[PDB]
Length: 123
View (cartoon, one colour):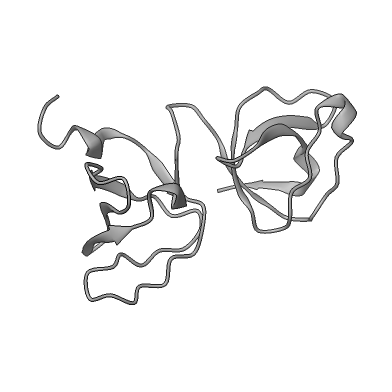
């Protein structure tokens, strides 16, 4: 790979990371995080604005070109028998399927399923 190739990938924060260590990154859910170094499985190094620092690798999600990122606006319980999922308000998800019957397939990074478009706001 070319040096710094990690930086060409689009990632968004899934969680609030409040910096405590001197070299910790600090970010909020939905922010774009540039990944600088992913060599270590425990902590990645990334950049947001004017800080380069360490952060948890599973606190960010990859967004491929054309992909849509949403913030859940209302907690909703889906019918699991027809591939629906339950999400809480304020969760961050990536859309993975075209809208059908007022539902879109979304990914939290831990789970995937259909969720209502009425309860999502694009970020």
